[PDB]
Amino acid sequence: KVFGRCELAAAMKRHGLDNYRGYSLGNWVCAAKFESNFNTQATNRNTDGSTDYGILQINSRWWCNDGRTPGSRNLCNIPCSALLSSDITASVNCAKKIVSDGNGMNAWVAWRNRCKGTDVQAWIRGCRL
Ligand code: NA
View (cartoon, rainbow, N blue to C red):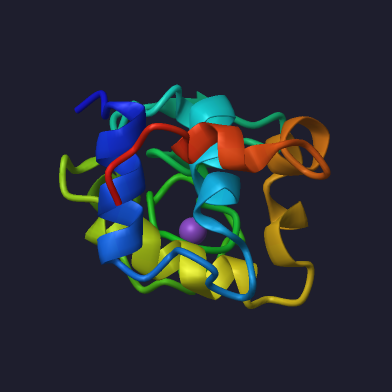
């Protein structure tokens, strides 16, 4: 599913991402924009042979099982395919674990490079939340 910006904002808020670990909703929407362009089905291969899955490009190196990332962990205890569903519940639950790991949203390199320090409130502008 390709979410609308305000559609994804509402879904993230419903699932308790708004101000989770102190990150405002706009941070999460900005991260999803640059990770996936709001596409739940987004997959990208990393140089290390790990793969990033779903709206928040969660990495098989640590967080989900895809069976093809040698030496990897599955800390969200989920198949990486569950991160591609039209229902973002699994992505959000796993994102809560990632952002709690000690480096906050710096875990998402595209958040650090493209959202951090910017006017992230713009991403929820005009949304009925
Ligand atoms: Na894994």
